[PDB]
Length: 313
Length: 312
Ligand SMILES: [Cl-]
Ligand SMILES: [Cl-]
Ligand SMILES: [Cl-]
Ligand SMILES: [Cl-]
Image 1 (tube, protein in one colour):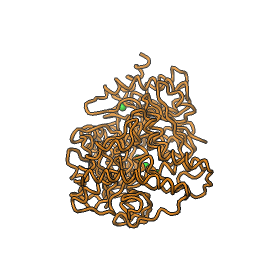
Image 2 (cartoon, helix red, strand yellow):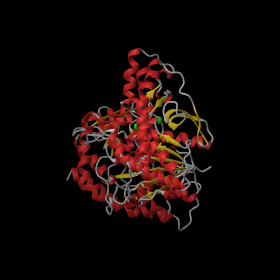
Image 3 (cartoon, protein in one colour):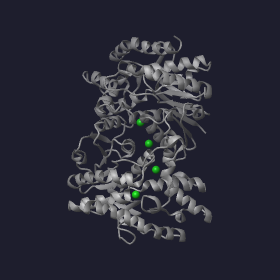
């Protein structure tokens, strides 16, 4: 089963780093298709094609992603602008909403059965945009639409391991909710081998929720979280590919589930041959987490409604 | 606890290289990032969120000394890249000065480090680095390298595709230098490959002009950055392994016996002091012997240009 992974937004900061990681991490025989408007894109593919791995790479540019999307099983969307010094979530939605819409319109007609991973922010909102564009095209499969939240997981694993003296490579931290601010809810109470003092929970939780700011407000001037976001995306794509290939994997991801909390909600999901295999429950929460969960819902629902309205008016 | 420093960590190669090193270096290795651009501390914070046991820190401003404290390996990728129509030598005027400045700081801050020059033109900038190191009275031939590893990746890739070999396990030696006519893949030493008369020259020319092929395909967006980062990361991993006591052999541009040129790329066993032993190029085919004769005058001029930038 020769998998095909397409990257829409392969010329941007996240996109190029993601192209590199996929070239190095994808299983042998996988096809990697890179697309973006900029004419540098075919050149990004040629650059990447020189790395000696058994992953076939092709690059495409111009206004039409259809050629790049041919036979795609996984479509990763990293197009648009990332959060940079002096930009609010409003700037992201302002620029990225129309970009995501146009790309999904092409996914809908070119590879409607692909699993789509939305990396472009704000994920809470941009995933709803994608769902509505797919619905309008009459091909919406909620098992195949994902908001990539994995970066919150990487950050959680890194900080928990640092603070509690655990193995950074083998520490597991579930993260539920959404992908921004108070919607990011790391389930610190479910981490093994970590004894928490009351005073550590809130500061660590706020640190994880506000981690993007540490990058933007770094000394001397700061920048965007380009590289960690690419690795988070690559890690997610890896899990999707495994699921599509028949291997059992579980990832916290933003999907349209039972709607008990919000239409879209990130929780553990077992991935399979059709994308979502089973949306697993969030498990037991501490009083702090239960409270944090209840607190985020109005913000999350608003993020969702903003994306739905962008397409439906 | 080994320490790897990247001078030019905010550029295209640099950022990608910071990412790969964070993911590929052994557990407990320190990674230090520096660039004049003020985004560099942010690049390190960005990379630090990736959960691996590699500790990373970033530095900016005009002084790289803080970034070089205790470095065992120093990778220099700073400077500008090619524009469509240029050869690697046309970058000399801008990059010669950037390399000199950085090496003056390496010379006084971490003179015992293995220095890998990625900044083009490598054939010349390595010579610049050597002479700067000599004026500081700390030049150690065993610790200065021109990174040619991208020629090896390209060779491995093109040979595996053309000859039906395993791309992960095909070994292709590459000698000479790092420029159009100085890159010499020793296709005759590749195992499991019967070469047709008409296959050798086109494949050699393809390996030699690969940098130009990426440059043209990017349509003004620069030269190779992503494959170059992996090539630089692989070379760094080999140096670290050598420094740690493991045996590894890599084709790399170093100051040897001067038989071909003062600096020449050939297989080198790496060890605790950097170069452990510069190995012979082995048997060459008639085509390879002739390709080697044809490059020597160009290679010698590339070196002399770098020597004259510092000495006069
Ligand atoms: Cl490699
Ligand atoms: Cl979001
Ligand atoms: Cl890697
Ligand atoms: Cl990871």
